[PDB]
Image (cartoon, coloured by chain):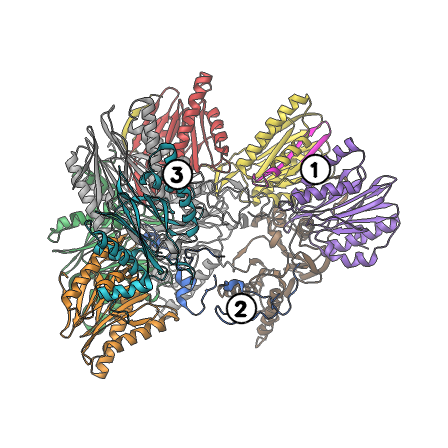
Chain colours: A cyan, C yellow, E brown, F purple, H red, I orange, J green, K blue
């Protein structure tokens, strides 16, 4: 799996692949690796599909109880803290989770919290998660800028996931992109790697070692 | 792996901790602060397992703040360190031990003396003039033994800390991405921009 | 450790050595190993020493309580039952092996108890690392209806065999004699065959030999 | 199949000015049973050398036999010349390291007078690594024996009274009789507190006049 | 031998004023099954030597063949072999100990414990022990297996030190051996009622009392036990 | 161990050996392995001594309470209690038991409870490590409705062979004869049953 | 054919914690099992990337000592060898 | 090994009418020496308790016995005697039979009524080791046993008792890798206690 | 663990290798050179276990020099890489395998073409435009895939190498103490002082 | 064990402690940890005393054959290479070695080669070996200078061993110092840590934490 | 009581190398276990201080397979049950 999320002047760009695998057998190529907690909060699942999907769906219900009780949205810090505490209380029980809690709040701005099985919770501007995280980092750290335009940030996320999909066996499928804006999150669609790769090779001229 | 160092100076306690956060093959962050302000004049730095460090740090901070709120005075660094030790020692025989080593540097406003306590994950408290946890002590202790004095001012303490940190950079294999240095003294807690 | 119990014509005599060892080291040269469960019920144990001590303390307290409750002298079988049930409850994790001997209105009794809760009637018994050496003497010399003197001599000499022939057994011989008609006779260091060899020189140091950095008077 | 045992022997070498002392208990052990009260393990090796391959008894016997063979061959080749202590030490080192990967589980000691006529003690580990020592205990009760001899023979941690710890007690020569007193007392203490020691004390004295054997009783319980 | 399969339990022996006595039961046990009852574990190797062997029975028979071959090879080109330059107990024991140690070092041990008992041609008693590890020692009394614990104390009560050997007569030593064998029968589960006894005397030579019986067993007290506890 | 129970014309004879061992060492050579759980019901202990003694005490408690509340139990009630206790704790327990008793309506009865905790009525039962060596002898020599002396001799010969072949069996052969006349203790010493 | 051990005297006690009571040395805590999807969570599938000096000297294993034995406690063999 | 991880030494001796208890000051993690001020001798009134072993358990037992002895002092109106304190420590150690503290304690004191010197030792789980001459615990238990056996003799007066115990501790510690960095010797009398710090090798 | 990188460019082959040598807790040296000149226009860089690396490197160098002397002409980089692969593959089923990964960067004077061969410790040879061994490939391959072009001159290759090395410094947990860069081309082998 | 060797303007300073330990029992405190291969070549051992002693005596014998045959001194490079090859051929056989081959040759000048069990062989200017190597590095790296005077270099080696002896349980005993000069090596004697420590505390005023 | 397999057809095999021939996977080579004085060389005492994917799903070990079996080879059980 490859997932990345980076803050920039226009908000947050969240990109993830689609492939899910069980050994060598590729189980599916259309796994939705973003759980949509609320119109302003976005989970990014990696590792174990069952654990992430179930516990972030439950986090959605906790968020709903939060608005109903307090009439204001759960902060990104609060949701990430709930998830971190929950995952921590099952440490050693076998949970397999890597989660970036991306959201936007009036009193927080754009914010990303990295959460994983071992209980860690990190606030940060750039995160890559999954088996392909290093390949995504190689591109993000070499191309990331705070003042990227929205189109350039979307393309950077798409390209960073494409690199990991190319180089990592467990990170193929298709690229799903989300843009967490001041007024919510925008789903910028699904891009199949089998076409994105050739489009990017032609336009950039990169992947010069790949025959074609 | 983490670096956490402490030097008790005539007037202040100088705590230094590494900025890197490593998870598996990749460094996730290079600006992490491995410390929590237990009280206005008490500061704690922690090292150990990923979730355990922060979870224990926040649990201890909440308990110390609850005690201070209830009794309406700041707990002495001795009391804070004893509570932390009792929580650590009480955990190793429980189902979920905290694999967390902590250095508690505080200024006792009642005794008007700086205090540095080293507490390992087993719950071994010891008051020290200079402290280090894990492998960070294997390089720094000899240098600290050589150069340390009781009567130093905070600036000589920072020079000694520079010596220790650059020795760690030289000989030690891991890249800990520098340290973040905080001084605990009569006036409270502050951070040094570039010691 | 070396324990022996020996029933004779009018009672039972239990004997043990006194050496106590941690690892290959003699932690104590004069450890008392015979324990009162009651005035006329005595036991000596092997295995995990701390467990033997704790269990004998527990059984003695419970038995004195029960004797006060019933207003009757304790039965040896009462101690046997309580001890074996307690040991069984823990499935041998208490690790207490005992030879329990005593006298009660029903006669003179000699039992052994094992960590897992099994027990045995016997006329002569042995226990501890020196069990085999002592049992050799007991088998060679035991007879029906020993007199008290012959019983004491036999038990003492079996313990001596264990002392001379086993490394984990040494120093002195403790003996306790329970007899039907009268009080038990505890014989601390009945035999002392291992007196200390004399020093060739007195290794006292002239005062001031040690170097002292600081001296203080403590407000206790 | 575990090819090693532990017979619980103890040996002690002390070197003086014109004498060397090698003392060792005669007890033989297997687990908690006493194999024999009198099994000597310090041997008069001839050429004014005394040896004791203490430790696992079978390996001790094998190493001793090998060294006797080697010294006899040395006598054969070198026209019956006297073998020096240092030469014997090197010979035994080569014997021990010849089995580097299947060592003799024995802590060997050889004691004698060196080419200058001064007492010398060479003590060995199962693999070799020989150090010439002024005094060296070995075996089961080495830990009990040795600190007391450091205190008495070397006067470590002893300071002249009235100097407040600035002047050590100077190291005087101990006469052979005094060293025998110390050896007897040390082995008596080891017998008292170690279960594997106390059957009998054998002492071999090496001096310019030749090797001399003395035997003393121990507690034997 | 990585493990023993069929074994003979124990051998007990002691030296007395004029010789040595050695005894061993005739039972070879296959685990807890008292399978073979006619095994002879005392191996005479001359008028002055008897070799008692314990442990694996197959290795015992191999050692017996080794001893027969020793005697046969000694007889070669040795016109004096019958009276002097005959095989002393010391030569037999040294050969056996060397073989045992070589086997141990080769990680293929002979799983036996061997007591070589006899008298040297000068009249001095020989009595030494050797086991699968090559560990050897001498004592006024020797025993193997459960004998080292059950029997050996009883024998030591008779001769506790070298000074007691001249004080010990044939009858005293033989009665001590018989009592020790009776005790071993009482307490050793691997033991048997039948046992062989050999006496080597510096004056009267080797006497070999085969298939003796354990006698004067004490069982009549067993009728007075009615259960555990009550 | 060599346990044995044989029903005969006038009742049942229960027999056992007296040797107990801890490895190769005979820790007790005159032990009594027959236990009186009730007036005319006797059990024999095999397997773990601690487990068998705990089960015996629990069964004695239950059968005493049964006798006080519901009248005298039968052999079947006793063996049923044994069965429930052994089965409900079969993972912890390691006890195999033979239960023999005499009730006038049924005369002598024998139930055997192997290590698994099942219940079986049999005309005769053999248990213990030494039983393996006398399965063939007992099978070819047992007969229905033997006389008391015939049954005693049969048990004597069977346990004699079991003691001969098993190193863990030995000592005196004890038997308890359960009949309308009463209970008779019998003891036979090695020189008596080994010279058969 | 094994011998009978009626008293369980020779009865010997997942791998055992070398030092009972201390969870820090518990096998399931010293070496916890990885998550079922740790291969997808970290690139190489892993969340993560002596005694005796110069002198060759020549503790018991809790898995072959009797149940009642406590490591480091005083223990006397009940029956001997 | 929890008992060997931190090292440390404790030794107690009985004089004619006085007792001495002494310990080393090193605290470390096997190889690394951490602190030279980890005093393992604690006192509760007139009874002194030295504790070797895992340092976390040393501190925990110091707190526990402080609490229990303070409650005893308050509700009894008298200080706990060495015998009663020994029994209390034994009972408290066995309370965790299956989860024991990895410590070896050593009690030393003078019974106030009888005035008789008293010393006792323990294992992990409370086996009382009452002895009349001297008690030893720690990583250098073997060295200390041998040294004290060689040096100790009955009825030592306080000055010679100090010299004997100090020499025993010094020579025992100099031969133990995980012990040293100075030592402290308490000389306890019917009316005073003298604490002294010994000079020794710092390696 | 060692960084060894190689980038084939239009004219030359650029090999980079870490300078740090580590043994357990301490970095023994930080100016180490993990390369050997197999021939005037052929260079080999190696990574792996401590003794195996240098022993295998010198064995290969001696054999290549022996072949060059005997045949009196320089072996092509293809032949050198084939020999190294043959040795490595023959080793893994012997008693003592070489746990050594190697990158052979050479200039084939007969073809006038640079050649870069990546050979893992099992003997898996493959010719590459850019190569990396161990964890060093996980961070750098994506960046090389992004920026690499067949037609680069050596200066652009050095710029790409700087990007790769600084990415490693950023996200790599270890402090590999920088790299030594050597260029293989028509003129021979040379080192870059500060690439 | 602690051993160090550093090159400087006046040659090489080689310092070693003396303690030898079996488990926690200090077997001896006067172990000679420097082997004198030849009047210009010096072997410093750590780890397994038996392996180092035996194989460096064998190295001395090979060195002797070398002078007999070739009429010139075995170079430090050659001696260290022979030792490295030998130790490597026993790699995995259980050898325990750490060695610094210090020497001086006309064509080499002062040279140090670090050799250990794994077959490693490193030329370098400063090396520390043994369980206490880190403390010696801490002292050396903070005080070492190329142009140290001979007295200052000797004192630096002595102090560096003293620090490791203080802080390391397995590195006590006494400090033996050697000075490898242009014309040979000089044995600058043995210093007992039990006295050196107090002398250094009084002269430097360091070790302020140590009571007294 | 076991069932006396005469043909050894039910016969089943240091731990076995999972991939025979390759010494890079031999337990004695993957875990050599150092040397007797490693604790004196290195300050720490040591010279050196999954395939499961995203979706959970429910080869044999040589030690539990007959000696004639080769991992990854075509094998037919001689009798099966």
Cα gap from disc 2 to disc 1, whole angstroms: 51 Å
Residue C62 occupies which quadrant of the picture? top right
Q: Which residue is mark 3?
A: A64
> Which range of residues does the magenta coloring cover?
C88-110
| Camera-side residue of H139 and E90 | H139
**Residue F40 in sight here:** yes
Q: Which residue is mark 2?
A: K67
- Labels 2, 1: one chain: no
What is the x, y in percent for residue A63? 38, 39
Is residue C80 part of the magenta span, yes or no?
no
Cα gap from disc 3 to disc 2, whole angstroms: 61 Å
Q: Quadrant of the C terminus of chain H?
A: top left
Q: Which residue is mark 1?
A: F57
What is the x, y in percent for residue E11? 63, 56
Q: Is residue F193 left or right of residue C164?
A: right
What is the x, y in percent for residue I48? 30, 63
- Callout 1 secondary element: helix
- Callout 3 secondary element: helix
- Give me the chain letter of mark 3: A
- Give me the chain letter of mark 1: F
Residue K37 occupies which quadrant of the picture? bottom left
Q: Nearer the viewer, mark 2 or mark 1?
A: 2
Is residue C104 part of the magenta span, yes or no?
yes
- Give me the chain letter of mark 2: K
């Amino acid at each position: 799996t490859t997932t990345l999320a980076f803050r920039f002047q226009g908000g947050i760009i969240v990109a993830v692949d689609s492939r899910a695998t069980a050994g060598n057998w590729v189980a599916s190529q259309t796994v939705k690796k973003v759980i949509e907690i609320n119109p302003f909060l976005l989970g990014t699942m990696a590792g174990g599909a069952a654990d992430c999907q179930f516990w972030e769906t439950w986090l959605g219900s906790q968020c709903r109880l939060h608005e109903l009780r307090e009439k204001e949205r759960i902060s990104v810090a609060a949701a990430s803290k709930i998830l971190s505490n929950l995952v921590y209380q099952y440490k050693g029980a076998g949970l397999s989770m890597g989660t970036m809690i991306c959201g936007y709040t009036r009193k927080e701005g754009p914010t990303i919290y990295y959460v994983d099985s071992d209980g860690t919770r990190l606030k940060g501007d750039i995160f890559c998660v999954g088996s392909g995280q290093t390949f995504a980092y190689g591109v993000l750290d070499s191309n990331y800028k705070w003042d990227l335009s929205v189109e350039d940030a979307l393309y950077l996320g798409k390209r960073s996931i494409l690199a990991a999909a190319h180089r990592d066996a467990y990170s193929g499928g298709s690229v799903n992109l989300y843009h967490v804006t001041e007024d919510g999150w925008i789903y910028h669609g699904n891009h199949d790697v089998g076409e994105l790769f050739w489009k990017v090779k032609e336009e950039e001229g990169s992947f010069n070692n790949v025959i074609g | 792996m983490d670096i956490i160092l402490g030097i008790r100076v005539q007037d202040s306690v100088i705590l230094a901790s590494s900025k890197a956060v490593t998870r598996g093959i990749s460094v996730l962050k290079d600006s992490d602060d491995k410390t929590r302000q237990l009280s206005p004049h008490t500061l704690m730095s922690f090292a150990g397992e990923a979730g355990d460090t922060v979870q224990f740090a926040e649990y201890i901070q909440a308990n110390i703040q609850l005690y201070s709120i209830r009794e309406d005075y700041e707990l002495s660094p001795q009391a804070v360190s004893s509570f932390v030790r009792q929580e650590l020692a009480k955990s190793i025989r429980s189902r979920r031990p905290y694999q967390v080593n902590v250095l508690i540097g505080g200024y006792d406003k009642k005794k008007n003396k700086p205090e540095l306590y080293q507490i390992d994950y087993l719950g071994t408290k010891v008051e020290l003039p200079y402290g280090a946890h894990g492998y960070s002590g294997f390089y720094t202790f000899s240098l600290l033994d050589h150069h340390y004095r009781p009567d130093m001012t905070t600036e000589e303490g920072l020079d000694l800390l520079k010596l220790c940190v650059q020795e760690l950079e030289k000989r030690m294999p891991m890249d800990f991405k520098g340290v973040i240095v905080k001084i605990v003294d009569k006036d409270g807690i502050r951070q040094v921009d570039d010691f | 450790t070396t324990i022996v119990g020996v029933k004779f014509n009018n009672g039972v005599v239990i004997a043990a050595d006194t050496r106590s060892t941690q690892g290959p080291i003699v932690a104590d040269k004069n450890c008392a190993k015979l324990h009162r469960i009651s005035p006329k019920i005595w036991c000596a144990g092997a295995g995990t020493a701390a467990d033997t001590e704790a269990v004998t303390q527990l059984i003695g307290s419970n038995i004195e309580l029960h004797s006060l409750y019933t207003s009757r002298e304790p039965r040896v079988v009462s101690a046997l039952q309580m001890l074996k049930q307690h040991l069984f409850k823990y499935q041998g994790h208490i690790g207490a092996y005992l030879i329990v001997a005593g006298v009660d209105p029903t006669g003179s009794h000699l039992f052994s108890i094992h960590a897992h809760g099994s027990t045995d009637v016997g006329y002569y018994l042995s226990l501890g690392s020196g069990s085999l050496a002592a049992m050799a003497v007991l088998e060679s010399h035991w007879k029906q209806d020993l007199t008290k003197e012959e019983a004491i001599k036999l038990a003492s000499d079996a313990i001596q065999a264990g002392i001379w022939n086993d490394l984990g057994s040494g120093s002195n011989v403790d003996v306790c004699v329970m007899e039907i008609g009268k009080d038990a006779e505890y014989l601390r260091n009945y035999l002392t065959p291992n007196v200390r060899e004399e020093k060739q020189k007195s290794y006292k140091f002239p005062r001031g030999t040690t170097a002292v950095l600081k001296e203080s008077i403590v407000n206790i | 199949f575990n090819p090693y045992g532990d017979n619980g022997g103890t040996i002690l070498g002390i070197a003086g000015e014109d004498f060397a002392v090698l003392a060792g208990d005669t007890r033989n052990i297997t687990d908690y049973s006493i194999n024999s009260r009198y099994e000597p393990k310090v041997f008069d090796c001839g050429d004014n050398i005394v040896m004791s391959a203490n430790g696992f008894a079978a390996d001790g016997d094998a190493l001793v036999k090998r060294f006797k063979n080697s010294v006899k061959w040395y006598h054969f080749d070198h026209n019956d010349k006297k073998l020096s202590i240092n030469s014997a030490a090197r010979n035994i080192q080569h014997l021990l390291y010849g089995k580097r990967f299947f060592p003799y589980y024995v802590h060997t000691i050889i004691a004698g007078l060196d080419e200058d006529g001064k007492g010398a003690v060479y003590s060995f580990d199962p693999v070799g690594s020989y150090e010439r020592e002024q005094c060296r205990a070995g075996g089961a009760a080495a830990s009990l024996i040795m600190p007391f001899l450091d205190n008495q023979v070397n006067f470590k941690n002893q300071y002249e009274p009235g100097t407040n710890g600035k002047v050590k007690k100077p190291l005087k020569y101990l006469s052979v009789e005094e060293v025998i007193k110390l050896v007897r007392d040390s082995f008596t203490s080891a017998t008292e507190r170690h279960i594997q020691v106390g059957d009998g004390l054998e002492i071999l004295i090496v001096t310019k006049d030749g090797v001399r054997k003395e035997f003393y009783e121990l507690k034997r319980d | 031998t990585q493990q023993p399969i069929v074994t003979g339990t124990s051998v007990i022996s002691m030296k007395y004023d004029n010789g040595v006595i050695i005894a061993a039961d005739n039972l070879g046990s296959y685990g807890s099954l008292l399978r073979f009852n006619g095994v002879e574990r005392l191996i005479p190797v001359g008028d002055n030597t008897v070799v008692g062997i314990s442990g694996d029975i197959s290795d015992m028979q191999h050692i017996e063949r080794l001893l027969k071959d020793l005697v046969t090879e000694n007889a070669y080109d040795n016109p004096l072999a019958d009276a002097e330059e005959a095989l002393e107990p010391s030569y037999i024991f040294e050969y056996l100990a060397t073989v045992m140690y070589q086997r141990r070092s080769k990680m293929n041990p002979l799983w036996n414990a061997i007591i070589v008992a006899g008298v040297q041609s000068n009249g001095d008693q020989f009595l030494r022990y050797v086991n699968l590890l090559g560990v050897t020692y001498s004592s006024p009394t020797l025993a193997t297996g459960f004998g080292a614990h059950m029997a050996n104390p009883l024998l030591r009560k008779v001769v506790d030190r070298e000074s007691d050997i001249p004080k010990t007569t044939v009858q005293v030593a033989e009665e001590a051996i018989v009592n020790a064998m009776r005790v071993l029968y009482y307490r050793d589960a691997r033991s048997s009622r039948n046992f062989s006894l050999a006496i080597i005397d510096k004056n009267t030579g080797l006497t070999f009392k085969k298939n003796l019986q354990v006698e004067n067993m004490k069982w009549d007290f067993a009728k007075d036990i009615k259960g555990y506890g009550t | 161990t060599s346990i044995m129970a044989v029903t005969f014309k006038d009742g049942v004879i229960l027999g056992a050996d007296s040797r107990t061992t801890t490895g190769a060492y005979i820790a007790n050579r005159v032990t009594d392995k027959l236990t009186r759980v009730h007036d005319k019901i006797w059990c024999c202990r095999s397997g773990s001594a601690a487990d068998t003694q705990a089960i015996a005490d629990i069964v004695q408690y239950h059968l005493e309470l049964y006798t006080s509340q519901y009248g005298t139990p039968s052999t079947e009630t006793a063996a049923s209690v044994f069965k429930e206790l052994c089965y409900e704790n079969k993972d912890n327990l390691t006890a195999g038991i033979i239960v023999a008793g005499y009730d006038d309506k049924n005369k002598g009865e024998v139930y055997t409870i192997p290590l698994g905790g099942s219940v079986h009525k049999l005309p005769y039962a053999i248990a213990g490590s030494g039983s393996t060596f006398i399965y063939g002898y007992c099978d070819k020599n047992f007969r229905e409705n033997m006389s008391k002396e015939e049954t005693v001799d049969f048990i004597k010969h069977s346990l004699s062979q079991a003691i001969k072949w098993d190193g863990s069996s030995g000592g005196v052969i004890r038997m308890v004869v359960l009949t309308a006349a009463g209970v008779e203790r019998l003891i036979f010493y090695p020189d008596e049953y080994e010279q058969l | 054919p094994k011998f009978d051990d009626e008293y369980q005297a020779q009865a010997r006690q997942a791998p055992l914690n070398p030092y009972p009571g201390l969870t820090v040395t518990e096998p399931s805590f010293a070496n916890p099992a990885g998550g079922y999807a740790d291969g997808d969570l970290y690139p190489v599938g892993t969340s993560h990337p002596s005694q005796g000096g110069m002198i060759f000297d020549p503790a018991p294993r809790r898995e072959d000592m009797p149940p009642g034995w406590m490591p480091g406690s005083k223990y006397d063999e009940p029956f001997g060898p | 090994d929890p008992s060997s991880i931190n090292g440390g030494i404790v030794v107690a001796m009985t004089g004619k009418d006085c007792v001495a208890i002494a310990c080393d000051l090193r605290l470390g993690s096997q190889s690394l020496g951490v602190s030279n001020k980890f005093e393992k001798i604690f006192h509760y009134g007139h009874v002194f308790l030295g504790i070797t072993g895992l340092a976390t358990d040393v501190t925990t037992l110091n707190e526990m016995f402080r609490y229990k002895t303070n409650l005893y002092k308050l509700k009894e109106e008298r200080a706990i005697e060495p015998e009663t304190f020994t029994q209390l420590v034994s009972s408290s150690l066995y309370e965790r039979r299956f989860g024991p503290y990895f410590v070896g304690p050593v009690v030393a004191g003078i019974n106030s009524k009888s005035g008789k010197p008293f010393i006792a030792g323990f294992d992990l789980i409370g086996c009382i080791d009452e002895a009349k001459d001297f008690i030893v615990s720690g990583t250098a238990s073997d060295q200390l046993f041998g040294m004290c056996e060689s040096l100790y003799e009955p009825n030592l007066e306080p000055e010679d008792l100090f010299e004997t115990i100090s020499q025993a501790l010094l020579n025992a510690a100099d031969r133990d890798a995980l012990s040293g960095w100075g030592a402290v010797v308490y000389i306890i009398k019917k009316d005073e206690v003298v604490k002294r710090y010994l000079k020794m090798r710092q390696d």
